[PDB]
Amino acid sequence: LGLIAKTKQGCDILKCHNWDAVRHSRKHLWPVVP
Amino acid sequence: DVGSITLALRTLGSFEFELTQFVRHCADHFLNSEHKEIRMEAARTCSRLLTPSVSQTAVQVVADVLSKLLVVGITDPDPDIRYCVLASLDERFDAHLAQAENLQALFVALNDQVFEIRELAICTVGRLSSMNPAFVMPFLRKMLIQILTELEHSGIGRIKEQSARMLGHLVSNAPRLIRPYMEPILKALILKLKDPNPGVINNVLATIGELAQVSGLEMRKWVDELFIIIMDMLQDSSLLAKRQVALWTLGQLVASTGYVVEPYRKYPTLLE
Amino acid sequence: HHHTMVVQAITFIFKSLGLKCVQFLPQVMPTFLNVIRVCDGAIREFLFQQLGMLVSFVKSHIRPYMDEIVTLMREFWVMNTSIQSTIILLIEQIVVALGGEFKLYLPQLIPHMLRVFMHDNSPGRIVSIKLLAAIQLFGANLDDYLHLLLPPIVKLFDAPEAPLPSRKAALETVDRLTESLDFTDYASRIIHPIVRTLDQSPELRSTAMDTLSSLVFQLGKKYQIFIPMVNKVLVRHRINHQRYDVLICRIVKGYTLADEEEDPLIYQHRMLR
Amino acid sequence: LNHPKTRQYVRADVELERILAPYTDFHYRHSPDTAEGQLKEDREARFLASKMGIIATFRSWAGIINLCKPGNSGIQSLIGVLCIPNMEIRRGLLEVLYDIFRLPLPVVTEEFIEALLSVDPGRFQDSWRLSDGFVAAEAKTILPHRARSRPDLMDNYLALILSAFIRNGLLEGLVEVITNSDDHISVRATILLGELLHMANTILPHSHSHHLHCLPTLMNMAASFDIPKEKRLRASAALNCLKRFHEMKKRGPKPYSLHLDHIIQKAIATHQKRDQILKDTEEALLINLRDSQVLQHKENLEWNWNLIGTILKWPNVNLRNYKDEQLHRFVRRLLYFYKPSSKLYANLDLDFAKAKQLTVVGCQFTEFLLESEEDGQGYLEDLVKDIVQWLNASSGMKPERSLQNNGLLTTLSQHYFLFIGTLSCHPHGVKMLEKCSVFQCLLNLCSLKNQDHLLKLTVSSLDYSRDGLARVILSKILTAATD
Amino acid sequence: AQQCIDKARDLLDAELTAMAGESYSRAYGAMVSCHMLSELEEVIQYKLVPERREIIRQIWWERLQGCQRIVEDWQKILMVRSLVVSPHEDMRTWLKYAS
């Protein structure tokens, strides 16, 4: 289930069922969420 | 030339049009300009003109100009340019200031000697808080501790009022972060009001009203002393001081606490 | 009537016994402080000095009795009287004795100190210089109070009206204590005052420039942007200085990449061992 | 504990959580008949066994699910024990916590800043010496991985465990220990807290990480003006340490060896060059070189090497407009001192107090020569062919002994390579390098099959940014060499 | 809306001052409209942040429990309060109104 959370649309799917996930990549280790 | 450049920059920042190379050309002026006014107005027009920040080609120029005016606003000697550029650094670029270098430059700017910059920078960072805790939060906590320390051990009224205005802009700019630390704030301030320049009282009242604003139903155990002290200030008001703000505070609490009808009997002289 | 000789006998006893006088504190100090509270006259000035000797002796076991001390040092501290020279020596011996737990009692002596920076009438302001030299020795004691105790210090050399030796002392004290404290983000509050005061005393050129040079050691590469602003002022008298030149040389021009902007405390630690 | 049939065979709350006995008990007596002659050593043996069992059971899913049931499971009991003032138990649990999270332990110490450096990720490693792992192993640790989107399940597991501990109020006990305990233990707890927080905003999803970093309980105690002052001041100091810890985290690892630092220096230089200041003619020049203390005498170890570097790197001193006799004497003194035939530069051994400064100063001097070409041709030529002379002598260009392995392994003559390094970068440098017998001499070196570490040092110094004779050398090395 | 309410404030203030000089009961007829007017800010808050909803809902009841018990004024106070609440959301006030 963490695997299927790699894409934004999948994260949208999961958030409907009360499961959090990380929304940033590893390119910069200090990411701001917009 | 001095009138020419100033007039041209003011007009460029003044009227509307529908330009992209002029700001890239603008790097020539203030980096080497020793005339204060042209640098200041170039800063104004460059801060103003590049608001639409969306297409995937022009981020380079806006990033470079951001670096340039941030460092200039950090560095130049006269405080007027400091204040004037800091004023231009409003929310209009809020979602793009979140680069790490910008934040470290802001932390450097956060502590200086003159106080208008104090207020403006602390407001800016407080607005900046909630979208990226990772950098700001530790420095914020140190600050908050520090302001508490002046507010209580400073034997000088000037520092006390200055810390109070700090606190006010903090509470205004940080909606959710200040919530967990309400108890020490309110208790220190209320003990300050019952102290055995009255502008300190003005600012503590403004701040405490704002704390009432942010906090709903969490001031239940402190409403009584607040009421007694406020109406003591109002009833038999020895000085015709800043009443309108005092009334605004007194009104603010009830609309938030949900404290509605008891005062008219338990403070019978209130209505008249 | 005869208290001077008995108290000097007491301190003689305490220097005589040495380390083993510790068990005798509880039944001697409380009465001593009660007398001080009730004592009177200029003999009190003598008494305090003697008390200083006492605190010089038992380094750590004075602690439970010292709290009361503070409020008595609060009470009889007249703002402008010759009594301040002795109270400064009291503080100096306190600092030498405690050394590390002193920060516990630091706040309560702060406010009065502040007003000394302003409401002073000493010829040449020698009391300010003395207390400033005393403040030099706090070291790792004032870790959290710099924000409040610096702005006064910078303020004293912001006035052109002050006697020149006082300004030299202020620059010296700010210059030296950095070898024990963290001074990174507190850059703006110092860079600008220095460039303000740089050309207002042709003798204070050297002391100020070396103070700045010492400060810029703690800050690593993040100084890089400040260079042109000082640069113009640097040669506007055709004044050149060595260590600062060395430092700007190895910042602007690549020396290494792992030797950049380390905490001052770790370097103090590495030079200690 | 997996199969329902298997699960029916085992009781509820007496069997598995037994293993954590010697910590939940203050006086655990494992065996009835024991020798009195040793008791405490029994306790250390028991603690080691129980610790290893605990870190064993938190690996399997069966352990994790069973040990964190919604009831009064043992994991709550462990955390509850943590807030009792027992001087060794609170220094028993912290080890378990560290090697659960697979963290590096700090050395026991009463002072914070030493313990901080003791666990810096950029700390030196024994395998990084020349003989062992010279570069590749160290480069594995210091520079970051190249993956941008691969999952790295390990962080997933750590996030799960971290959330599991966060649920049961671990931070509360951590703050309790940081506040009310001894210093030997306060430093350990503070370091753990900082490391966990740094992991938080790195692998933890926002919703479960947006309120933890506020630090309610510690901060609340930090500003109470009625509590005894000791707690207040120590909490303040703890917060200061946490901030400095985080700042060191954002510092980032930095190289200790010279080669990697030079390589990344060239890399960042060329990538900067991809995408697009004081004159000091004569007066301060004379001032400093007079003050340089070098002209008084040729004896080493009495020179102001920092001032030397300042002269050598100053921008507009280039010896091309500036023909100064004192400068000539200075540069000749340096030329002599740096000579391998001088038997001074190469005869200071390693582990000298001021050596790395000397090496960077030497690379500085070589770069200065590279700057001043059209009149300084000879100065480099004699020195470089002297270097190649010493090179052939040590390689075995003579039939006398041909074994000088105790010459380079303990002397800085190994660092002579760096100069060729800074010679192998600039386009004029390569024409200088091919002026003398260098590339061909190196290709003659690679034909050797007895001296090995020569290859180790030489392969790590050449540039490969531009096509040239260096590349075929490395191709032969990877095709014609020892195993 | 805020500017509208601000103008309404002083346009009531005039007659409130003209009416207050005699006696309290005489000013009651304007005070009911004033308490009418200032409640709209609470309507704004109810519409904006859905987290305060229960607290303001309770304090509406407590504020309204103290006014003069005449049907006509309860009519309009509930009718403006009904702007954001369905009758089936708050049964208790309507029962007392009916009684």
Image (cartoon, coloured by chain):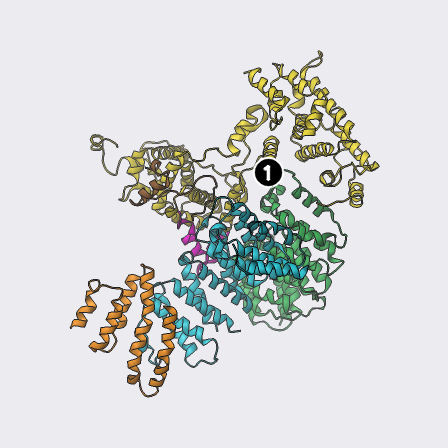
Chain colours: A brown, B cyan, C green, D yellow, E orange
Tell me where residue D340 appears, x and y as whole percent: 73, 25
Residue at the (32%, 45%) spot, across then down: A15
Region of the chain picked out in magenta, as a range:
D209-238
Q: Note whether residue C57 is visible.
A: no
Q: Is D431 rendered above or below residue C85?
A: above
Q: Is D351 rendered above or below residue C110?
A: above
Specify whether D179 is left or right of C241: left
* Residue found at the far bottom of this picture: E22
* Residue found at the far right of this picture: D325
Specify whether C16 is left or right of A25: right
Tell me where residue D467 appears, x and y as whole percent: 61, 25
Residue C212 inside the magenta-drawn segment: no
> Callout 1: few (<14), some (14-19), or many (20+) C-alpha neighbours within 10 Å?
few
Q: What chain is tagged by disc 1? A: D
Q: Note whether residue A24 is visible.
A: yes
The residue lying toward the viewer, choosing from C95 and E94, is E94
Please tell me in which quadrant of the rendered image residue B117 appears: bottom right
Give the SS element for disc 1.
Answer: helix
Specify whether D217 is left or right of E25: right
* Residue found at the far front of this picture: B18
The residue lying toward the viewer, choosing from B196 and B218, is B218
Tell me where residue C212 appears, x and y as whole percent: 67, 52
Residue D228 inside the magenta-drawn segment: yes
Q: Main secondary structure of the magenta part?
A: helix
Q: Quadrant of the N terminus of chain C?
A: bottom right
Please tell me in which quadrant of the rendered image residue C12 appears: bottom right
Residue at the (38%, 74%) spot, across then down: E7
The residue lying toward the viewer, choosing from D369 and B221, is D369
The amino acid type of the residue labelled 1 equals Gln
Residue at the (47%, 42%) spot, across then down: A29
Residue at mark 1: D272
